[PDB]
Amino acid sequence: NTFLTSSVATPPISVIRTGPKWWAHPERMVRQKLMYFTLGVDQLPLRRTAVIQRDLQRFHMCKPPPRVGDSTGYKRSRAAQLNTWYRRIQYQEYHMQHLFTRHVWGLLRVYPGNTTKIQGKADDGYVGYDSVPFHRYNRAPLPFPARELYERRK
Amino acid sequence: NFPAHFIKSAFTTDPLKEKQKARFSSGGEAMREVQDTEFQALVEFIEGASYDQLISG
Amino acid sequence: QGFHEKAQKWREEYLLDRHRALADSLRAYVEFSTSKRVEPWDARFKPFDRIEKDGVYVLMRYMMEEKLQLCNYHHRPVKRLFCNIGLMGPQITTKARWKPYRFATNPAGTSKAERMYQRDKTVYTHGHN
Amino acid sequence: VGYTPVNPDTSPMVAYSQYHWHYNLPQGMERPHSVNRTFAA
Amino acid sequence: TVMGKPLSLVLDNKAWLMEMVLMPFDEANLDYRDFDAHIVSEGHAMPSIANEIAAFALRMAVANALVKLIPLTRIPLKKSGLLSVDRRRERGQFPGY
Amino acid sequence: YYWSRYRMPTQMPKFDNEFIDPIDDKFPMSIRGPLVRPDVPEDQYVDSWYICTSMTHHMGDYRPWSASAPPNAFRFRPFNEFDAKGREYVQYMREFARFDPRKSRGNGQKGFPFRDAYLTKMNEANQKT
Amino acid sequence: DNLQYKRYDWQGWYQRMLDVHNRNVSLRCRICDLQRLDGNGVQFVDMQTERRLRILAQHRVGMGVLKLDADKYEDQADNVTFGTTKLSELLADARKA
Amino acid sequence: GVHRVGYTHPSTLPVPCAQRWDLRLARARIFQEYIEEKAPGAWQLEDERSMSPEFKTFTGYPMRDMRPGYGQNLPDYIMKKRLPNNTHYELFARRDIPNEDNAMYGKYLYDMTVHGTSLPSTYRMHKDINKAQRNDRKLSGNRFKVLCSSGAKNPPSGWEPIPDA
Amino acid sequence: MRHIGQDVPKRHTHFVLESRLMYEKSFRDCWLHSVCRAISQLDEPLSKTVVGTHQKMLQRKVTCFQYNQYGLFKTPYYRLANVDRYHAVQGVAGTREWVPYVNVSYWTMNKMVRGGNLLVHRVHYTGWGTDSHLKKGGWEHRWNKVLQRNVLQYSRI
Amino acid sequence: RKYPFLRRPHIKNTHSMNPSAPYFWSFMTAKSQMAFLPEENYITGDWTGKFFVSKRQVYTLQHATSGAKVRVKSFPSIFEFNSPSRWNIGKEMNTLTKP
Amino acid sequence: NRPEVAMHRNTVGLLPAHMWETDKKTGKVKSVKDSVRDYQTKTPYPKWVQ
Amino acid sequence: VSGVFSKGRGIGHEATTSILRYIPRARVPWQPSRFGRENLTAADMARLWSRGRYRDGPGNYNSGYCTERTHVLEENTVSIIPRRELEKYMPDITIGPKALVTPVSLMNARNGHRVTHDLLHSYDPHIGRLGKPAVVDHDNITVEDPNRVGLNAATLDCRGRIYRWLRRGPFFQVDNYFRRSVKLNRDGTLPTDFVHEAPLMRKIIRLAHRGHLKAACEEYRRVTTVPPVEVYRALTACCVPGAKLADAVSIFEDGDSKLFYVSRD
Amino acid sequence: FPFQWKTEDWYEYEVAKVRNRRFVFENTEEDGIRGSEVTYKIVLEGFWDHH
RNA sequence: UUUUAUUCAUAUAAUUAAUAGGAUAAUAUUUGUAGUUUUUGAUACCAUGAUAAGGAUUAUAAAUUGAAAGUGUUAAUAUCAUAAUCAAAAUUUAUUAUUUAUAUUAAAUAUGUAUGUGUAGAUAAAAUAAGA
C-alpha cells in the first residue's frame, strides 16, 4: 500500500493489552467490519472482541472488588480462566484480521510493506526498495526493478 | 558574630527613655484615648463555625 | 616542538589534494547530470502500471518521448514535464507513485538494488555520483 | 548582606518590613509635604 | 448544531462520539427530535474537536441545559452522573521532562 | 542616623513534621471541615508574598457572602433570575431583538450584533424551515 | 512618572522616553459629519465621494469612522499637524469624484 | 495560470469610471507606499494560524509574512523594520547599571551634599579595616604597590620616616 | 589600576558598564548602517529620477562610505554577551540561564527571589501561570499578543 | 546543554567540511553572487601593517597575481597560504583551513 | 547549474576538461596542472573601471 | 616599591601652584594622594589610550596601528605584512577623516551624534576632558586621537566618565553642541554674519522674494547658524499675500523665543 | 434557532469584529450615557489589585 | 547405606578610581570651574547557602460536582560575609534523552559520514486525561 518501509513485529499480547487506543479503536474496528462485510463473511470474532472491549472499558474506572473476600482457591482461578479465554478470542480476531488483510491485498494487487508475506503470490515475504540490498531473513539479493507481483494491465 | 537582639523587655528599657515616654504615654492618656464553665467551653468551641472562624482542635 | 611547521605542511598538502578533489567532484557532478538515469516512477501503481502498449505508455512514447530523452529521465524534470503536459491531470502527486530519491538517481541500466552503495565515495557530491 | 548594599526602593523586604508600610493597608498618602511654598529659592 | 455546523459534521460522523451527546435525552426519557440545541465553543478553538473528552464536555453541557429547561430531568441525569464534572487535567509544560 | 529608624524593639508575648500544630492538624477532617481559612468571598484574599498562605487585604474584619450580593439574593447572584451565562445570553438575545444596522455607525465592537443569530439569519439554507 | 523616575537625573530621559512612546495621535472624523453642504452650495461629500474615500482608505476607515493614527514625529504637536495634512490630502483626492 | 494582466482606460470604456489600478496608484501616492513590482500573484498565502477563528491562536491579524526566504539583510526588511531607538534596549542601556545608585546621582556629589566627604565603597572600607588589624598584629609581609612610584623612589626633602623597632 | 584600587568584589562587573557603550553606539549607528545596506543591496531602480548607471555608482559609493565608517557598530544583538549587573554571571538568552525582564542571570534571579529583593508571585513550577495568553498558546501566543498591542492596532497613516 | 537554534555560543565551532561540488557557491558564502565583497577585502584607513588577514575575506585573483603573502589564524600559531592557485576563487578563507 | 530546478541542462561544455589530467582508463581526474601560470586575461578588473 | 607608573607630572600652572601651596587643600580622607589620568605623561597616556580600545579599536594587534613589526604567539614569532604589500591585494578605499563625520542635520537621526567613531565623542567639556576642557573637532577626527575627547571604558578614570555619560538628560548632546557653537557676541551683535551660511541666506531671500515659500522653508530646514533678521522679514513678507497667518506666526516664533529674539523686528 | 451559518461569513464576521475596536466615536450628540464633548480615561497602575 | 527508553559535541589568551545644571527665568565668561607623586586580598581562591535524591494519612452512609501533592537528612556542588600572585576571547575538544526510503540547500557562515535480520550488559522513569 502507501506504507512500504521496513517494519518491526510485536507480540499479539501487546496489541491486545493496548485497549481503546489502537486495538479497540472504534474507527479501526469499523474498517475491519467493512472489510469482512464487503467480502460477505460473518464478523463473529470481531463482535466478540468488540463486546469484550466495551465491557472492559465501561468498568475500567471502577475499583476491583476486595480480593480478600474472593477465594484464592477458586475465584482467582476462575478469573484467570476468563481472562485467558478472552485473550484467546482476541488472538483469533487479530489473526483473522491479518489473514484477511493479506488476502485483500493479493486480490487488489496491493504491494505490502517489506518482508510481508501474502499467501498465494509471495509466499516468502515481498521486499522492495529497502535500505539493505539483500532480502532480510533470506539473504537473497534484490534487483532494482524489485518484483512485479501482478500482471501489468489495469 | 551574632548581634544582640535582647528579646527581654527588661533589657531594652532605660530610665532616660522612660522619662520622655511617660509624659506622652501614661494611664490617664491611655484612658483618654481608648474606649457554667462547661457551657462556656462548649459555646467557645461551637462559635468557630462562624463565617470568620474555623473549627479548632 | 615543530608542531606548527608540521601542521602548516599538513594543511598545505591537504589543500593541494583538495584542489584535485574539487576538480574530480565537479567532473563527476557534470557527468552525472548529463548521463541518462533510470525511469523515476514506480511501475507498481495505477498510472504507470498498464502494459507498455496501452494507457500512459503510448502517450509517453508518442507525445513526450523527445522531452523525456532530453531530460535524461531525471526525476524532477520528468515530474515537471508530466505536470506541464496535463494529459494526466492532477494525478501525478495524488495517485501516481514515484521511486525514492537515491533509487531514482541510479544510472540507466542497473538491475541491482546494490547500486547506490557502489557509487564513488571519494567524490564529495551529496549523492550525485 | 554583602558588599553590594540592598536597594531600599524596590526591595519587598524593606518595603513591607515592620519599619515601613505593608501592602495590606489603605496605602494612603503618609504626609502632605510642602517645601517650595514654605520656603522657596 | 455545534458552532453553526451540524453535529455529524462537527464530530465527523462518529457514532461513539455522538452517542454521548444523545445520552441525556435517553436518561431523561425524552425525545431527541423535540428540542433545538446549539453549542458555542468558548475554550481553545481547534479545527477538530472529534474526541472523547470534547464529547464528554458536550454531553455535560447538554445535560445542564436539559436540567435548566425541565427541572424534573435533574434526578435521572444526576443519578446517571452526567452533571458530575471530573477535575482531571493534562500535565502542564515543564522542561525537566 | 538613617539606621536609627530600624531599632524599635518588640516585646515578647505574655503567657499564662515542622510548622504544624498537632492538635489542630490532627483534628478529624469530617468535623473540622476541609477548609484552611474562613469561607468568605475570595475577593477578600490576596496571595501573600514570601509566605505560603493567603491573607486578607482588610486586616481581619471578614465580610460574609451576603455583604456582596443584593438583599435576599438567590445563591448570592447579582440577579436571581439567571446565572452568569444565562445573564449573558439573555442579554445577547434581547439586544439582537432590537439590533438595527444603522445604529452600528460611530461606535466600535458594540455595533456588532449577536453573531450566532445574525449569521444564521444571513444563511440562506436557514430561511427554508 | 511619580514613583522612582522623578526628582533625579534619570527622570528627564525617562520622561522623554515616555513622550516618544506616546507620540501617537489619533484623529477621528465621521462620514455623516462630512456629508454637509459646503460654502459653495453643494454637498461636501456625495455617495461617489464617500465610496472613493472608502476605497482610498482601505483599513483607515471603519464603522463609518475615518481614523488616522500618526506616529510620524516624536511629539504630538507635530503628529497632529502631520495627521491634519494627510487628512486634507485624502479629502482633496476623494472629492475628485 | 500564466497570463498578462490587462488594463482598460476609462476613455476607452463605453461608460467612464475610476479604475481600481488608478485608485491604487492614488492611494499609494497619498500614503507614500512602495509598490513591489516583483510580488508574485501565486503567493497569496493567508496566515491561517492567526486569521482562522477555528484555531486557538486566532488574533485577527496576520502575524507572519509567509516567506521562507526572509531575513534582515534584504532592503524590504530594512525599509519596513523598526529602529531600536527609544526602545527597551535604550531603557536597559541606562537602567541596568551594575551600581544602582549611579543613574540617579553622582556618588561624589551625593556624598559631598549629604555628608561632608566622599565615602569609599563598603569593600574598600572592609579592606582598610583589615589592613589596620593586620598592621596592628604583625606589620610585616606587606608590599608597597602604588600607582606612581616617583614619590616613593624620590621622597620629598625633609621627609624622615621614624623606625618601628 | 591593576587590582590596587577597585572598590568592587567582582572586577568583571565593569563588562556591563562597557556593554552599555555598545548599546549606545548601536543606537547611534543603527539608522546609517541600515540605510547604507538597503541602498547598496537594492537592485531594482531606486525611483523614476535615478536609474541605471547612476544607481550603480550611487550603490558603490554608498558601500564605500559604509566600509570607510570606522567604529560603526554593526553587530547582531544575540552575539552580545549577557552578564548580570550584580554578580557578573553570564547567561544565554533564550534559556533558563537568563531572565529577560530583570536582565539578570538565573543565579542572581534565584538569589533575589529566595531573599527579599524582588517582588514576584510564585506559581506552579510546571504550569502556564495566571496569564490567559500564556494559557492559550504559550510563549509564542504571548509574543504575538505583545506584537499586536505594540504595532498591529494603529491605523499607521 | 542546549542553546537557541542558530545562536550557538561557540562561534568557531563551525567545521567547514570539504567543499561540495553540486553547490560550491550556496554554502559558507554570500546567498547572492551579485552582492559586494565584505569589508575585509579592502583598506579602510592608513594602517601600519596587517598582522594576518581574517578568515572572512573572500579569495580573489589578485591574491595569486600580486604574490603578497597572506596568512590566517588556525589551531597553530599562523597558517600562510603558500603556493597560490586559481581554483579557489570566490570562496572565503574559512573554507580552506580544515581545523 | 544547481540541482534545485535545472540540473539536466548541465553540459560537458561548461566543464573545462583541459586544466587537469584525467585517467584515460577510468575517467577520474588524476592530477591538475597549474592555473595561475601564464594565465590569459583581457582585463583583471572590470573594463568600465578606471 | 611596586609602582605601576615610574613617572608623573603635575597639571597646575607653575605661576599658581607655588602660591596655592600655602593654602591647605582638603584631600579625600580615605585616599589623599590622587593620581588621575591627567597626571600621566604623554607616552604613558598614548599607550594607555591605545590599550583601552582592545576589543574594537586599534588595541588588538591584528586590528591595525600596532606599530609592532613582529608578534610573539604560541612560542613562534611572526613578522608583520606592511601596508604597501597589503594594498596590492586589498584595494584601498580610504576617504579620510571627512567620512567619519556626518552632517549636523543627521544629529537627530543619529541620536545626538555627528562623528562615526569607535568611541562616543561627547559634546560637553566634562566627559572627554583631559586637563583642558573637552573640545571635539570634526576636521581632525582620527583613530590616533591626539585629544582624548572620546569615551572608552578601559582607561584609568573610565568608570566615572561612563557613569556621567549614561546619566545624561534628553537633548544633552544637541544642547551642548548648539550652546557651544552658537552664542551671542561680546559686542552684543547677533551671530548672523557667518560666511559658511551667507549664500544659503541669500538663496532663501531670493526664493522668498520670488514667492517660493515652500522652497525657502525647505532650505531653512538645513541651516545650522542663526539666520539674520532679513530672512524672517522676507519669509513673513512672502507669507503676507497668501494670508498664511499660521505659517507667519510659526516662522516668527521659531526665531523669537528660540534664536536670541532675532525675529523681534 | 438553532444557529447555522457558513464558514466564509463566520470568518469575515470574526475578523471584522476583531479589527473594528478602536473605530469608536466617543464624543457624539446622543443623549443619555453616551454623547459628550470631551472624554478622559485615567489608567491607574499598581503592584496589587486591591491597591 | 505493569509499562517506556538510553551512540549525545568544544573547555580559556594579559590589565577596570571625580563632581560639574543652557530658549520663553530681572542679567555670575562660573563662555571654556585646570593644587601630580605614601600605598597595597582574590588578571586564579569567598565557605558558606541553596539544590539534588526524597517518603507521611483522615475523609460512615446519604447529598453535593463535590471535600483534597507533601518534607528531614545524607550527599555532591558552587558564582555569597570571611585567608596576594593570577580562565573567558586566538575556542578541536571529545560535555545522556537525534530527522531511516513517492518528491530532499533562497537570504546573518549554518555539517560527507555508523545501511547491515534492529540483535548484549547495565541504567533511568511513571500508577497524575486518560483507558495494569
Image (tube, helix red, strand yellow):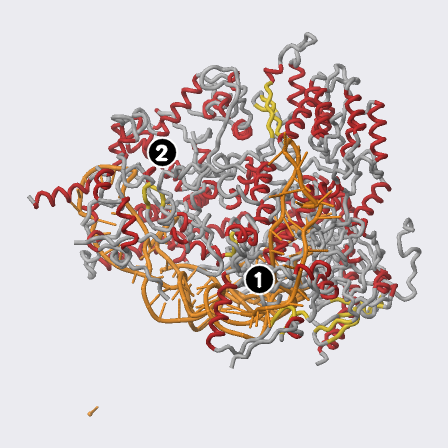
Choose between H155 and I108: the one closer to the eye. Answer: H155
* Chain of the residue on which disc 1 is drawn: I
Q: Residue at x 81, y 65 (%)?
A: J49
Location of residue M49 with respect to H20 vertically, above or below: below
Residue J17 makes an appearance in the image: no
* Chain of the residue on which disc 2 is drawn: E
Q: Position of residue H1 (x, y in %)?
A: 71, 34
Choose between B27 and H86: the one closer to the eye. Answer: B27
Q: Determine whether, in the image, residue G25 is placed left or right of residue L96.
A: left
Q: Determine whether, in the image, residue J21 is placed left or right of residue D5.
A: right
Choose between J93 and F38: the one closer to the eye. Answer: F38
Q: Residue at x 34, y 44 (%)?
A: E87
What amino acid does circle 1 point to?
His
Location of residue J13 with respect to L171 vertically, above or below: below
Q: Residue at x 41, y 28 (%)?
A: E38
Q: In the rendered view of the protein, which quadrant contains the C terminus of chain L?
A: top right
Which residue is label 2 attached to?
E61
Location of residue G92 with respect to A86 vertically, above or below: above
Q: Position of residue J76 (x, y in %)?
A: 71, 72
What amino acid does circle 2 point to?
Ala
- Label 2: element kind: helix
- Label 1: element kind: helix
- Tell me which corner region of the image, top left, top right, bottom left or bottom right, holds residue A75: bottom left
Q: Position of residue A64 (x, y in %)?
A: 25, 52
Residue D25 makes an appearance in the image: yes
Question: Marks 2 and 1, Cα distance to the nearest angstrom?
Answer: 62 Å
Which residue is label 1 attached to?
I12
Q: Position of residue D15 (x, y in %)?
A: 41, 48
* Badge 2 density bin: few <14, some 14–19, many ≥20, Cα 10 Å: some
Q: Determine whether, in the image, residue M45 is placed left or right of residue G81.
A: left
* Badge 1 density bin: few <14, some 14–19, many ≥20, Cα 10 Å: some
Q: Determine whether, in the image, residue L121 is placed left or right of residue M13.
A: right
